[PDB]
Image (spheres, coloured by chain):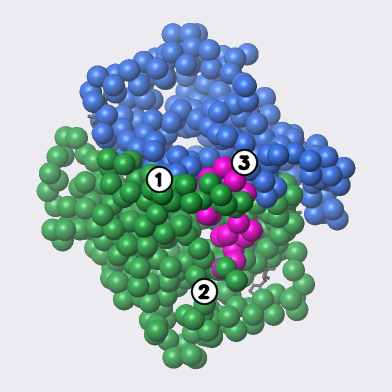
Chain colours: A green, B blue
Amino acid sequence: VGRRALIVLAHSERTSFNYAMKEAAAAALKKKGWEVVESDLYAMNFNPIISRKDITGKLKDPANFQYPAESVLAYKEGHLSPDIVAEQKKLEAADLVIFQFPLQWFGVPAILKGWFERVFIGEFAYTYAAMYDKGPFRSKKAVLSITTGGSGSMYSLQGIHGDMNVILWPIQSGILHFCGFQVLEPQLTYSIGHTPADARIQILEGWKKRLENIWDETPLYFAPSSLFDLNFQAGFLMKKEVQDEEKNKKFGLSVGHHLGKSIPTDNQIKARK
Amino acid sequence: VGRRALIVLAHSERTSFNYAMKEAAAAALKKKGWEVVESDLYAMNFNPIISRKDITGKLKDPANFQYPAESVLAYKEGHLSPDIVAEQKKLEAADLVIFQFPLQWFGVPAILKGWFERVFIGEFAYTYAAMYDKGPFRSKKAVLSITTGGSGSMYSLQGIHGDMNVILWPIQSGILHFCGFQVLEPQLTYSIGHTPADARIQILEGWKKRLENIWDETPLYFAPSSLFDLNFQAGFLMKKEVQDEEKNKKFGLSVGHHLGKSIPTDNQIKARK
Ligand SMILES: Cc1cc2nc3c(=O)[nH]c(=O)nc-3n(C[C@H](O)[C@H](O)[C@H](O)COP(=O)(O)OP(=O)(O)OC[C@H]3O[C@@H](n4cnc5c(N)ncnc54)[C@H](O)[C@@H]3O)c2cc1C
Ligand SMILES: Cc1cc2nc3c(=O)[nH]c(=O)nc-3n(C[C@H](O)[C@H](O)[C@H](O)COP(=O)(O)OP(=O)(O)OC[C@H]3O[C@@H](n4cnc5c(N)ncnc54)[C@H](O)[C@@H]3O)c2cc1C
Ligand SMILES: CC1=C(C)C(=O)C(C)=C(C)C1=O
Ligand SMILES: CC1=C(C)C(=O)C(C)=C(C)C1=O
C-alpha cells in the first residue's frame, strides 16, 4: 500500500481553486493516515531552467557541454544542485505523487515543465535499460489533477480543441510512465471559471472522497514494454509476433500506439473496465 | 510572401547542433533576402514564469488575482512587462517564425513553454471569437525544427515511444494553430547524438535548402473551424451536418479530431499530397 505522498502544486495564488484543491487533498489524505509533503513550486520560487549550474563541481567536458551526460554523472557522483537533490529526496520517499495544476497552453505550466527537466535526471528517474514499466518509479503511482478554462465539450472528440486524451498523452506516457510510474485516472475539472459556488464545493468534496481509496484504483493502460524489442538493433520497435497478432484487432493499443487504427476510448482518462 | 523571419531558439549551448541549426537558418534565409530577427531565450536570459509582475501597475483585482483577465487588460491598457512586449513586437513583424529546440520530455523546453505562456497573451495571440484559422496570426507561418536523442524508429507507429504525430499535436494545434498560425511541416532530425560528422553536415545543408522555398510550402492540415459551432451554448461542438457527413469517412480529420477512426498518416508531420 502507500502511506507517503507528495503534492506538487504549480500555481502562484493562494486564492486559486488549484491551491484549494491542494489543501483538500492534503487534508483528505492526512485523515486517511498518509504523510503528505508538498512542493509548491511557486512558493519555493523554484528554478525551472536546466543549466550547467545544476552540476556543483567539475564537468567532464566543459567546452562541449551536454546536459544529459553531465547531469547523469553529477547524480552519480553526488554533484547535483542542492535544490534538485532536495526534490529527488521527496520523490524517493513518496508512494503517491499528485500534480496539481491549471492547464496552460495544452500542457503543464513552464515552472512544472522545468521541475521535470531538472529533477528527472537520467539514472535517477529513468534508464533506457529500464524504460517505462521497468523504470525506477514503478513502485510509485502518479495522478494529474488539472483544472481548465475551457469546457469539457471543447475537449470531447468533436470539441474544437480536440480529444483531451491526445493532450494528456505526452505527459502521462512520455514523462510519467516513461519513468516507471503507474499513472491513475486524471482528475479533470473543466471550466472551473464557469462553475457555480455550490458545485465548486462538491468538486473539492469529490476529489477528497476519491483520495480515500486512490491507492487501490486501477491504473491507465499503456502498451507493456514486453511487446517491444528494447534493443537499439531492432530499433525499439514492436515485436513481429506482436505486430502480427495485432493486425487482426479493430482498435490500437493506446493513444500513442494507435497503430493507425482507432484509439481506445478515453485511453488516457479512464482505466479499463 | 514573406520578407521577415523570427527564429526562437531554446538551447543554452553555443556548441549545440540546435545553435548550428539556428545559424544555418539565419544564413540561408538572409541569403534569400529575408530579414532575420532572433530570440535566443537562454542568451536573453528570458524569464519563463508568469507572475503578477508581468503587469506593470495596478491590478483590477489584486485580492483574487487571475492571470488571464489581468494580462489581457494589461495588454489592452499597455501595462505588460517590457520584456514581454518586446517579444510581442517581434511576433507582429515576423512573417515566418522558426522554433529551434531539442525535444525535452516529449515537449518543448520549459524556457520556451514559459515564453508562450508570457508572450501569447489573450487578445494579442488569441481572440476566442477568432480561434484557430481565424486567429490573429493567420497571416504568419510557424515551423518547428526539433532535434532528438531518440531514433526515428522510436517514434514510428510501432516505436516504443509511440507515434510522433501525437507528441506534436498539443504544440502545433494547441499552441501555434490555436493562434491562427499556418504550421508548416516539422523539421525532424532524430538521434542527432548518433549521427556521423558527415551526415550532420548534410542535415545543416538540407535545412538551408528547404528554407529557400519554405514560404511556398503547403501547410499541415487542421480541421477548419467552419465545421464547428463556435459558441458557448453549442459547446464549440462539430456541426451536426458535419458529424453526419463524416460518419461515412474512413479516416478522422486529424490527430485531435480522429473522431474515433484511423488517424490520417503523418497528419502532423506531412502536408496533404
Ligand atoms: C498562461 C495560461 C495558459 C492557459 N492555457 C489554457 C489552455 O490551454 N486550455 C484551457 O482550457 N485553459 C487554459 N488556461 C486557463 C486556466 O486553465 C484557468 O484560468 C485555471 O485553470 C483556473 O483555475 P485556478 O485554480 O487557477 O484559479 P481561479 O480562476 O481562481 O479559479 C478558482 C475559482 O474557484 C473559487 N475558489 C477558490 N478557492 C475555493 C475553495 N476553497 N472553495 C470553493 N471555491 C473556491 C475562486 O473564487 C474562483 O472563482 C490558461 C491560463 C493561463 C494563465
Ligand atoms: C531535460 C532533457 C529532456 C530530454 N527529453 C527527451 C525526449 O523526450 N525525447 C528524446 O528523444 N530526447 C530527449 N532529450 C535529448 C535531447 O533532445 C538531445 O540531447 C538533443 O536534441 C541533442 O542536440 P543538441 O543540439 O542539443 O546538442 P548536442 O548533443 O551537442 O549535439 C549536437 C551534435 O552535433 C555536433 N555539432 C555541433 N555543431 C555542429 C555544426 N555546426 N556542424 C556539424 N556538427 C555539429 C556536436 O559536436 C554534437 O555531436 C532530452 C534532453 C534533456 C536535457
Ligand atoms: C476559458 C475562458 C472561457 C471559457 C470564457 O468563457 C471567457 C469569457 C474567457 C475570457 C476565457 O478565457
Ligand atoms: C489564458 C487564456 C488565453 C490567453 C486564451 O487565449 C483562451 C481562449 C483561454 C481559454 C485562456 O484561458
Residue that badge 3 annotates: B263
Estimate the x, y position of residue A103 in percent, counting from the top left: 58, 57
**Quarter of the picture holding the C terminus of chain B:** top right
- Residue A151 vs B41, above or below: the answer is below
**Left or right side of A238 for B223:** right
Q: Find out whether residue A266 is within the magenta segment.
A: yes
**Which secondary structure is most common in the magenta stretch?**
loop
- On residue A240, the disc is 1
**Left or right side of B197 for A167:** right
- Residues drawn in magenta: A253-271
Estimate the x, y position of residue B21 in percent, counting from the top left: 36, 25
**Quarter of the picture holding the N terminus of chain B:** top right
Residue that badge 2 annotates: A218
Q: Residue at x 28, y 46 (%)?
A: A231
**SS at circle 1:** helix
Q: Residue at x 49, y 81 (%)?
A: A216
Q: Label 3 is found on which chain of the structure?
A: B
| Residue type highlighted by circle 1 | Lys
